[PDB]
């Protein structure tokens, strides 16, 4: 049943400290085995406790707080508070709080008239220990003017849902998902925050980020990252729809993550690249609308690169691996670099740079003048048995516009395929054109590239850069 706050002494007048009265309703709801704590319209002032871990209000299992709506019910920290406050509404440290939530209310951190790191909504059990909160809901909720973190569900929370909510004008990050498991952020807006719109961090996995919007933030619109410590990377991160635009850094940044997906998003107006991918094992970048990024300088709308943490906390080198980039509309250059394993990399209207590294890769440039780089003779080859797998294929090579970059391979030019030349051949059925080194190396391998289509007559020497000098003259991108 319902427990109205005013029936416990809450005023909601903007002056009286209602922390005890509102906490009384929570305790009554928790003691009743569960219930809804209801707040009619008004601004309810609230103060913290002795320590930061006390937060301000402590929500408990099976207790739900329902206000009169965003802007109508406002829970605001008192003027003059000067202590770190981890969660204006929070669950208890060391307790597995479950089946609780908050709806239709505004949390105001009052950073203008307070000092100290303030977080709005804090969940979780115990940092670096096993155990979790679970079944946590936030619906139609505004968190604003907190000095550090607006929505800050923390380690660990399972089945957190935040939908139709807003975080804005917060000191650091509007949304932080810190070791969230099996959780959903849907149809949220995070804007004009000090650093990040959304920040998924600290081993979070199986996260859906659907139709979220982030703009005007001082840093990334959305960042998915390991964080500063040598712990398990996040994985299984599905970013669907929404829009990440006009942010002070990349629109979407993903680093040291496994099996990430970014699909159907509108990404524009950011100061850095629209999408940046740094050492990600399994990356899908499909059907996005990416334009007018790198407003603060920069040469690329999309950046795929490694993450070298050898001098960092983990001491490891993290390659970007198992990448699929298809169907994107990109009004600018895409830098699509991957490594060992099969990669499918499609460029777009821009002058793109493509390199699948080791393994059998399928590359396509799309519109514009694109450079297909082959950095190592073992990145595309046919073996002693003639096994045509491990040979790359370029779908749409356009003679006179695109470029094959062999500048590091040490071949002199086109020829009969021996003595450092490459032979230009056509397969029997007329469907594929091969660049082949007929000279086997010590392991029986032949460097070889397949070009879909018949290009033995249209492809000329100026379409291939065989050394650094030729790459300087013929390079179609400024990304090298
Ligand atoms: O990696 C990056 O790139 C980012 O790193 C960011 O630094 C993060 C850290 O990595 C963590 O995420 C950190 O999480 C904090 C969290 O913000 C809270 O401060 C929390 O505080 C709890 C204490 O750790 C402690 O467990 C405490 O237990 C109490 C208990 O409640 C009770 O009172 C009992 O009687 O006594 C114990 C006690 O030991 O005192 O409860 C606290 C609580 O609030 O629940 O601790 C975690 C933590 O990991 O320590 O937050 C920082 C951060 O600043 O965000 C950051 O640098 C960012 O810029 C980077 O991007
Ligand atoms: Ca808890
Ligand atoms: Ca202040
Ligand atoms: Ca590859
Ligand atoms: Ca292109
Ligand atoms: Ca092209
Ligand atoms: Ca390859």
Image (spheres, grey):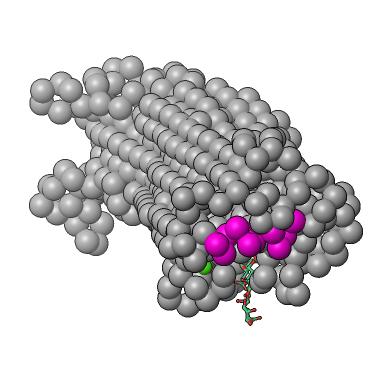
The reply, left or right, for residue 110 in relation to residue 336 is right
Tell me where residue 235 sits by quadrant: bottom left
Q: Residue 137 appears at what percent x and percent y?
A: 48, 49
Tell whether position 402 is magenta: no
Q: Which residue is drawn at 84% across and 61% down?
A: 81
Q: Tell me the chief SS of the magenta region.
A: helix
Q: Where is residue 472 in the image (x, y as percent from the top left)?
A: 58, 35
Is residue 467 or residue 100 the one in the foreground? 100
Q: In which quarter of the image is the C terminus?
A: top right
Residue under the image location 68 percent in, 65 percent down: 55
Residue 179 in sight from this viewpoint: no
- Whether 241 is drawn above or below 366: the answer is below
- Magenta residue check for 21: yes
Q: Foreground: 480 or 413?
A: 480
Picture layout, residue 195 above or below residue 212: below
Apparent side of residue 351 relative to residue 110 in the rendered image (left or right): left
* Residue 428 position within the rendered picture, expressed as x and y whole percent measured from the top left: 10, 26
Ligand 1 sits in which quadrant? bottom right
Is residue 398 visible in the rendered structure shown here?
yes
The magenta segment: 18-28
* Residue closest to the eye, 314 or 356: 314
| Residue at figure coordinates x 16%, y 43% from the top left | 388
User: Outermost residue toward the front?
Assistant: 7
């Amino acid at each position: 049943m319902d427990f109205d706050v005013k029936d416990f002494g809450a005023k909601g007048d903007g002056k009286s400290d209602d922390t005890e009265a509102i906490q009384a309703a929570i305790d009554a709801a928790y003691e009743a085995g569960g219930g809804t704590v209801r707040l009619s319209a008004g601004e309810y002032r609230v103060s913290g406790g002795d320590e930061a871990s006390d937060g301000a209000l402590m929500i408990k299992s099976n207790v739900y707080m329902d206000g009169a709506g965003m802007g109508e019910t406002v829970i605001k920290l008192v003027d003059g508070w000067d202590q770190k406050l981890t969660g204006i509404i929070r669950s208890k440290n060391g307790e597995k709080t479950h089946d609780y939530g908050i709806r239709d209310l505004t949390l105001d951190g009052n950073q203008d008239n307070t000092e100290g790191e303030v977080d709005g909504f804090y969940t979780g059990y115990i940092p670096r220990e096993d155990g979790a909160d679970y079944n946590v809901t936030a619906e139609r909720v505004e968190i604003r003017e907190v000095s550090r973190y607006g929505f800050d569900p923390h380690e660990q929370t399972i089945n957190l849902t935040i939908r139709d909510s807003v975080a804005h004008n917060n000191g650091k990050d509007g949304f932080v998902g810190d070791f969230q498991i099996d959780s959903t952020f849907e149809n949220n807006v995070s804007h004009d925050n000090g650093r990040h719109g959304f920040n998924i961090v600290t081993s979070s996995h199986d996260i859906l980020l659907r139709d979220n919007v982030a703009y005007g933030n001082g840093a990334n619109g959305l960042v998915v990252q390991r964080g500063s410590e040598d712990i398990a990377h996040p994985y299984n991160i599905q970013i669907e729809g929404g829009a990440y635009h006009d942010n002070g850094a990349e629109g979407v940044l993903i680093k040291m993550t496994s099996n990430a997906s970014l699909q159907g998003a509108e990404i524009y107006g950011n100061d850095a690249a629209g999408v940046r991918v740094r050492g990600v094992d399994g990356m899908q970048l499909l059907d996005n609308d990416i334009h007018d990024n790198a407003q603060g300088g920069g040469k690329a709308e999309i950046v795929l690169e490694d993450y070298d943490d050898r001098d960092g906390v983990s001491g490891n080198y993290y390659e970007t691996l198992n990448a699929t980039v298809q169907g994107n509309r990109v009004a600018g250059a895409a830098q699509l670099l991957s490594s060992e394993g099969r990669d499918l990399l499609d460029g777009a209207a821009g002058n793109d740079l493509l390199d699948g590294g080791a393994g059998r890769d399928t590359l396509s440039g799309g519109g514009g003048a694109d450079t297909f780089r082959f950095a190592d003779r073992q990145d595309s080859f046919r073996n002693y048995e003639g096994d045509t797998s491990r040979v790359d294929d370029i779908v749409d090579f356009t003679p006179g516009a695109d470029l094959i970059d062999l500048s590091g391979l040490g071949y002199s030019g086109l020829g009969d395929g021996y003595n450092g030349t490459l032979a230009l051949l056509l397969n029997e059925d007329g469907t594929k054109t091969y660049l082949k080194d007929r000279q086997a190396d010590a392991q029986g391998n032949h460097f070889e590239i397949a070009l879909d289509g018949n290009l033995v007559d249209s492809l000329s020497a100026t379409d291939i850069a065989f050394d650094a000098t030729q790459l300087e003259l013929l390079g179609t991108t400024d990304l090298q």
